[PDB]
Amino acid sequence: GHMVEADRPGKLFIGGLNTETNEKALEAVFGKYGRIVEVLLMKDRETNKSRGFAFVTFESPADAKDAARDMNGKSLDGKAIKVEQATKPSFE
Figure 1 (cartoon, rainbow, N blue to C red):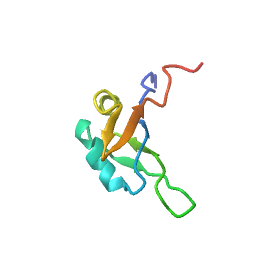
Figure 2: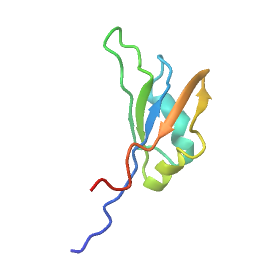
Figure 3: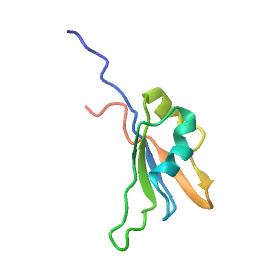
């Protein structure tokens, strides 16, 4: 057909995290802004500790954007966490 609907910034980018977290707990971090259907934790290789960064996705891009408009630059369990938009509006 015609299609000009190809934008969906449903991805976010998290930093500053704990070492002893899991994806089920990230549901409690961000799901309240607009529901999650995909979480990606990422870990070390030394001794399986979590690293101080992870990835969370949302069902909708309007639910993704909002999860970075309140929760950015706060504490979480006494660590200092971050959220950013890991995109740009256009790139060519």
